Image (cartoon, coloured by chain):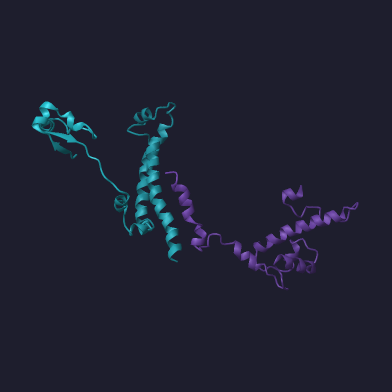
Amino acid sequence: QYLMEGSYNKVFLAKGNIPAESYTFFIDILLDTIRDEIAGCIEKAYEKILFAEATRILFFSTPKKMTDYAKKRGWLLGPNNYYSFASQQQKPEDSTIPSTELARQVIEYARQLEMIV
Amino acid sequence: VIDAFRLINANMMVLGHEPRQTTSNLGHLNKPSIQALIHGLNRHYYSITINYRKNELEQKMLLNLHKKSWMEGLTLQDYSEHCKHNESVVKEMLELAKNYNKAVEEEDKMTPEQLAIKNVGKQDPKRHLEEHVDVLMTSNIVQCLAAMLDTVVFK
């Protein structure tokens, strides 16, 4: 219900570790999947943001867990955020002209078109 | 229209008659309309046919064009000229578009010529719009093909 609604806060999967029959294991692998999905996206989202802000809505427990987890993903390789590489690429969609490369072979489309007539 | 003939002898006509020239050959006898031409033919000569000699080599000479035509097609048609054509095509299309719109309300019957009288004028308004779309298409085809093609090859 929560996951479909998009209230990640409400999930009851980052607290479904404590009550378990032997469920705790399954809950943990599923949790890791949830954390990743958000983690890649956030990079694109914004530039160099606080460590504390980057633990909060990254579903992390401590800045130590964030450092190791962020590093594999490609942000916070050091002790300083590196969100900035990823973020800048996304925002301008209407700027890019390698020209000939981008045109993508005008010749082919033309040739398809001409043949019928 | 050109003809070849052969003279016929006076003694030949009386005894032989003119169909004797016709034997052991093609035997086509020409009529070059009526009037003086035909009348004079009959009183004077026998006309016989023309064939053309040809050879493969002879053809090959004729067919030959230009070195320059090689680049001609390639040539990147100016945007300016293209734009003139593009403007010309959209304006005719708009005028016809209306006609097209009224036309489709009817036309439940086959026979496209009847639809042409109804929609008014020779040929259907659907066909008029296509004719214009096609002319633009031809200009466009040389330009776009040429545009990429030129840049890559000289580069």
- At a point 9% along the width and 30% down the height, the residue shown is B11
Residue A13 picture location, percent across and down: 81, 54
Report the residue at 61% width, 65% height from top.
A88
**Colour displayed for chain A in the image of the structure:** purple
* Residue B145 visible in this rendered orientation of the protein: yes
Q: Colour of chain B?
A: cyan
Coordinates of residue B118 in the picture (x, y in percent): 36, 29
Quarter residue B47 falls in: top left
Image position of B70 with respect to B99: above or below? below
Looking at the rendering, in which quadrant would you find the C terminus of chain B?
bottom left
Question: Which residue sits furthest bottom?
Answer: A79
Residue A2, percent across and down? 76, 49
Q: Residue furthest left?
A: B10
Residue at the limit of the structure toward the right, as seen here: A21
Residue A52 placed where, x, y %?
Answer: 74, 67
Residue at x 35% of width, y 34% of height? B123
Q: Nearer the viewer, residue B39 or B147?
A: B39
User: In front here: B115 or A86?
Assistant: B115
The answer, for residue A16, to whether it is visible in the render is: no
Residue ID at (49%, 56%): A105
